[PDB]
Length: 50
Length: 50
Image (cartoon, rainbow over all chains, first blue to last red; front, side):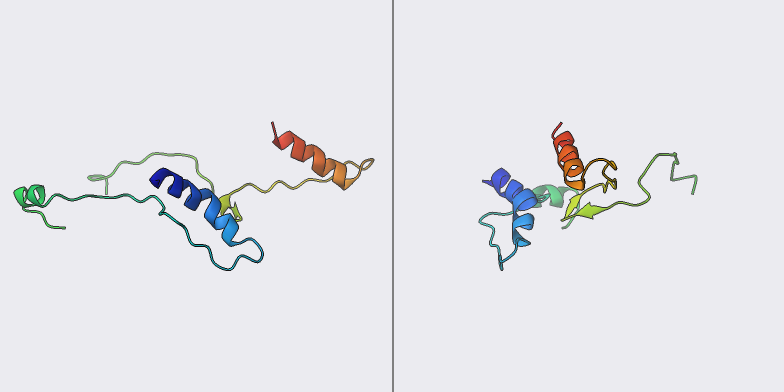
């Protein structure tokens, strides 16, 4: 679902949102993002915090 | 600055343009005097297909 949602957000949502007569577009997904999933144990080992 | 940096020469775009939210290059041209503008547009559209 994530790849499809990213493709829709990147290539299909924006052109459709500016189509004449389209007021609001609700994406049933989410665009890609750089997710940094932190580990508290590893952060604690190196004396690091978020 | 020479202690913590390196420098190089590279090519880049002095002016970037986008059309309808996507990166684009604008091409300006005219139809040949004998022929119409519509024929030139159709031909260049067919060329873009290649």
